[PDB]
Length: 50
RNA sequence: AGGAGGACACAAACGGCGCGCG
Image (cartoon, rainbow, N blue to C red; front, side):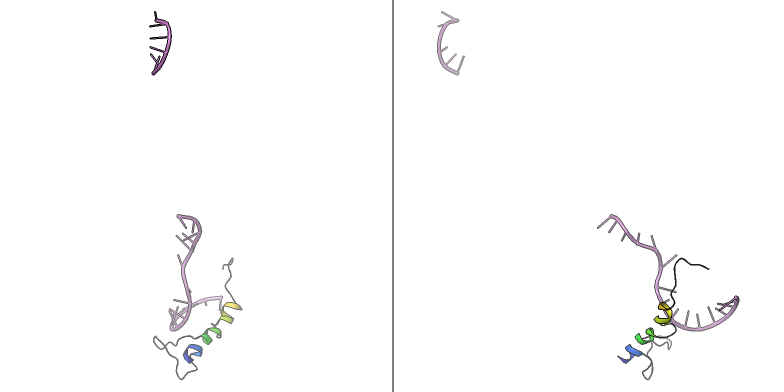
């Protein structure tokens, strides 16, 4: 349950690849790649180009 | 003779590593 909630606060994060720890719910909530700064504050918009 | 009867709808995703540009 600890690994499911806030993976990384444990002694060591679990992984299923070359030592790439699995992202948890708390990992998805916060962070520069998290929802707050990735999809809510700044979001990709249609009707645009470059 | 007479007479009688007789299927609609429906268009490609997510995480690393590297490089590069503003």
